[PDB]
Image (cartoon, rainbow, N blue to C red; front, top):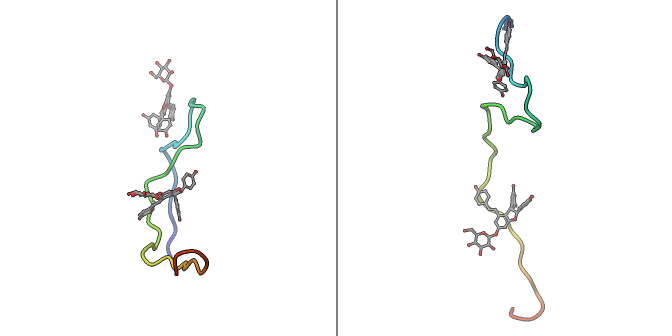
Length: 40
Ligand SMILES: OC[C@H]1O[C@@H](Oc2cc(/C=C/c3ccc(O)cc3)c3c(c2)O[C@H](c2ccc(O)cc2)[C@H]3c2cc(O)cc(O)c2)[C@H](O)[C@@H](O)[C@@H]1O
Ligand SMILES: OC[C@H]1O[C@@H](Oc2cc(/C=C/c3ccc(O)cc3)c3c(c2)O[C@H](c2ccc(O)cc2)[C@H]3c2cc(O)cc(O)c2)[C@H](O)[C@@H](O)[C@@H]1O
């Protein structure tokens, strides 16, 4: 069982923007979408 202790480390203090944290990794590769109409 993992338990994370939080003591010092603020990600937002005085800045008007929704801050992006250091974990950004989504699965992307194939995106299917064939148009059947003009050029087949
Ligand atoms: O000398 C401190 C100067 O601070 C500035 O404001 C600030 C004071 C403090 C934070 C104050 C803090 C205080 C007590 C405490 O226990 C913990 C944190 C921090 C500021 C600004 O921006 C940092 C910030 C904000 C958003 C982020 O996404 C990332 C960083 C923040 C920051 C956070 C942090 O984890 C570590 C830092 O060294 C700084 C003021 O504008 C100045 O006037 C002042 O002189
Ligand atoms: O090389 C860039 C080419 O861009 C194309 O337009 C685009 C390529 C891509 C994105 C490409 C992408 C690629 C790799 C990758 O790992 C991730 C994302 C996207 C486009 C256009 O608009 C989407 C958009 C833009 C602003 C927003 O606020 C919201 C959406 C964006 C979009 C983002 C997304 O998270 C998921 C999507 O399906 C689409 C043009 O049609 C091409 O001509 C051009 O060659």
